[PDB]
Amino acid sequence: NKTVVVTTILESPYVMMKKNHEMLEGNERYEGYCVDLAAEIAKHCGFKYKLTIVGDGKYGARDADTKIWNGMVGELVYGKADIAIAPLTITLVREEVIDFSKPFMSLGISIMIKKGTPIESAEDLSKQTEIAYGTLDSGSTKEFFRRSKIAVFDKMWTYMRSAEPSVFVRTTAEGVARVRKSKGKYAFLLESTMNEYIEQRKPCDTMKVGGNLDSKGYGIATPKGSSLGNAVNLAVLKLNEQGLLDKLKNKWWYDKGEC
Amino acid sequence: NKTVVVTTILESPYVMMKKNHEMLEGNERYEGYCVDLAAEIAKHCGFKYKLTIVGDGKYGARDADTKIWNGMVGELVYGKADIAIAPLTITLVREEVIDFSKPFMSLGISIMIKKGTPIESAEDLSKQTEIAYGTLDSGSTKEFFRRSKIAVFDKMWTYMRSAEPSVFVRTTAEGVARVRKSKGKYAFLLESTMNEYIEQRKPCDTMKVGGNLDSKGYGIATPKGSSLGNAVNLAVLKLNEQGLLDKLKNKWWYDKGEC
Ligand SMILES: N[C@@H](Cn1c2c(c(=O)[nH]c1=O)CCC2)C(=O)O
Ligand SMILES: N[C@@H](Cn1c2c(c(=O)[nH]c1=O)CCC2)C(=O)O
């Protein structure tokens, strides 16, 4: 009856503006993993959709003061969009306010260094200060450290929230650029699948080291009680079971790898 | 109000009989990953429970003809249990008849060989016959090959269902024993986490080879429309975020690894 409003975010290689996008219109000006994923889900759920880029360019966090949800989560919570299709992490605080399909991608927080950086693990970073390190300000990664009770991760958090100048960045591209220009003096803590993607991008000067600090997954989100919830969940399971999600990952990560 | 009836299955190291269990009673008779997980979930959701072993010793499949569900899924579907806590794979067909919490453990189908077997991937396997290979005669792994349309997995499936003598086994233990006693002439297709578990068990003559064929997860299951659903799902997320699920895996997989 109505065109589904999808909220997503400009994050390579999930959703990106096609080259010379000015000559394009609607959904055709975007390309990426979640762009392809959106098409598949729509086709399987039988619905027309419109891709929109989240107004504040954020994922989703609740302000402790105003208790207001921002980012894509907020878009769904306050009814500005019908569904969110992006690298959105399934978390307890978010699951309490919105619904998540089963994960369409598995991942965990990882460490990105400039090749050559004498860092092999989180503990390595924790017991040193020569090499600074941070995370995306805002996001599930930052929250992980902020809420963790585990010795190593709590030590890291006390360091990061106190660091000066700030060790946090506004976007992934900023973290990546910061690592690249810090001559091995800055390590970026980000989600493994993004870490892996950048490792295959010129100038091929970064790499993921160590194991993941945790294990989470990205899920398709819908506002609570949404009628699309059930169908989308089944669509995600179906797509994964047919190997489609694996192919989409290959296509955007390695088929187009530049290293 | 009522003691929650938990249905689980004897599958090491998820649920196992303690030494001299005849000396013990109730839940104290069992130990393992799911036993610990069950206790953690119950504590967080605030309910008393009784661990029970699924009658037919199966995970859950629908009979094509009678369309009746067996195993743990069947116990939930037909109201014989309130919740299922075990290495139960989240699949589309199952999600259509029961509810699953988000995954508490990630996995994928993998290849188990006796040390020295000249096999490294599903493709090697599919391109030969001297080395027999199969899976459990029941479960998601078997179902994966049965419904797969990917050339490699289809070829493998056509071989397995035609194979004589039968390459399917009644249980993991049998799959392992067959691998262990086949002089390298039999490979077992099983879920990664079990493969990894057995690789750390004496005689230490088996190992995992190649990447996983797929990417899936185990979830706590409840009957569709169960009131326990929400709280359980939230509990799994919390346990994961606090890092308890990772601790339980280390404890049952590596802390007591015998190799
Ligand atoms: N997925 C997270 C957002 N997010 C993302 C990346 C990261 O490194 N850290 C992080 O928190 C890379 C892409 C998105 C969320 O939902 O908050
Ligand atoms: N997890 C599956 C059951 N199962 C299991 C293993 C396997 O190798 N294959 C399989 O289908 C080892 C652990 C249990 C299900 O839910 O049906």
Image (tube, coloured by chain):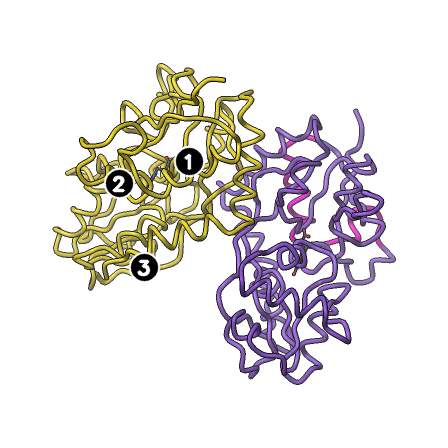
Chain colours: A purple, B yellow
Q: Circle 1 sits in a helix, a strand or a loop, which is it?
A: helix
Alpha carbon distance from label 1 to label 2: 36 Å
Q: Does the residue labelled 2 lie within 8 Å of ligand 2?
A: no
Q: Nearer the viewer's eye, disc 1 or disc 2?
A: 1
Q: Nearer the viewer's eye, disc 1 or disc 3?
A: 1
Q: In this view, does A10 lie to the left or right of A250?
A: right
Taking the spot 46% from the left edge, 43% from the top edge, the residue there is: B217
Q: Residues within 10 Å of mark 1 (few under 14, many from 20)?
A: many
Estimate the x, y position of residue A31 in percent, counting from the top left.
72, 54
Tag 1 residue = B38
Q: Residues within 10 Å of mark 3 (few under 14, many from 20)?
A: some
Identify residue type, mark 1.
Answer: Ala
Taking the spot 40% from the left edge, 50% from the top edge, the residue there is: B213
Give the chain letter at badge 2: B
* On-image quarter of the C terminus of chain B: bottom left
Q: Does the residue labelled 1 lie within 8 Å of ligand 2?
A: no
Tag 2 residue = B160
Q: Is residue A95 left or right of residue B206?
A: right
Estimate the x, y position of residue B183 in percent, counting from the top left.
12, 56
Q: Is A131 drawn above or below residue A84 in the view shown?
A: below
Sequence-wise, the earlier of marks 1 and 3 is: 1
Estimate the x, y position of residue B124 in percent, counting from the top left.
30, 57
Label 3 in the same subunit as label 2: yes
Alpha carbon distance from label 3 to label 2: 19 Å
Give the chain letter at badge 1: B
Q: Give the range drawn in magenta.
A: A24-46
Q: Residue B192 carries which label?
A: none
Identify residue type, mark 3.
Answer: Val
Quadrant housing residue B257: bottom left
Taking the spot 87% from the left edge, 58% from the top edge, the residue there is: A22
Give the chain letter at badge 3: B
